[PDB]
Length: 71
RNA sequence: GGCCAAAGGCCCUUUUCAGGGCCAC
Ligand SMILES: [Ca+2]
Image (cartoon, rainbow, N blue to C red):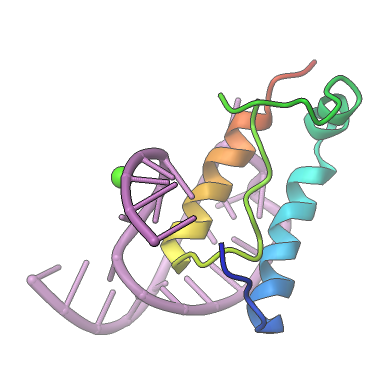
């Protein structure tokens, strides 16, 4: 993917990532998975990539829903 | 390079496994 430079898009997309990193599922995710994480393994959406608005948001929707494997 | 995931174009919000607005069709 080809990097994004606009802070008005990066700061916002960074925000959405923190929200998912705030959850207890993400904290129970990193604590149990050491970057050998495959796909199918829910993965943080690439902030620097070239995505449309509805496009990146939709990846966050599925990311946040996907994270909820925990207790 | 290319292919898949995501994706109508943009925006706000911790109603956030969520809610909402305009434009378009
Ligand atoms: Ca699709």
